[PDB]
Image 1 (cartoon, chains in turn cyan, red):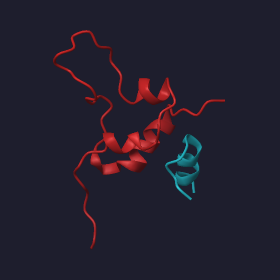
Image 2 (cartoon, helix red, strand yellow):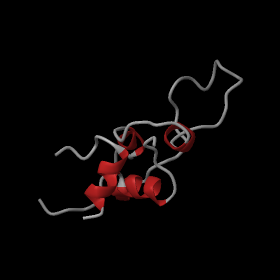
Image 3 (spheres, helix red, strand yellow):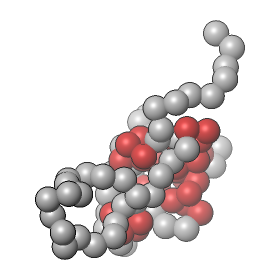
Image 4 (cartoon, helix red, strand yellow):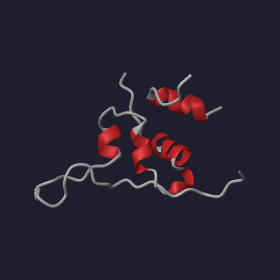
Length: 16
Length: 70
């Protein structure tokens, strides 16, 4: 899904 | 709990988004000539103190681009 949605999404997107 | 970005999380996003573009903390937004009285704020006071949007991270990203194969 879209990464730029919330502050949590950014972390999960990067931390993978 | 509110959703904010501070510390490594803030720097991580800018580095993950802009990366080699060279993100800047202080940048214009409204007007810095006609208005005299104005406080200091950019990405910290805007997203750390208040909940902003991740899309803002792109604004700070420079227009330049690193090297890549294409």
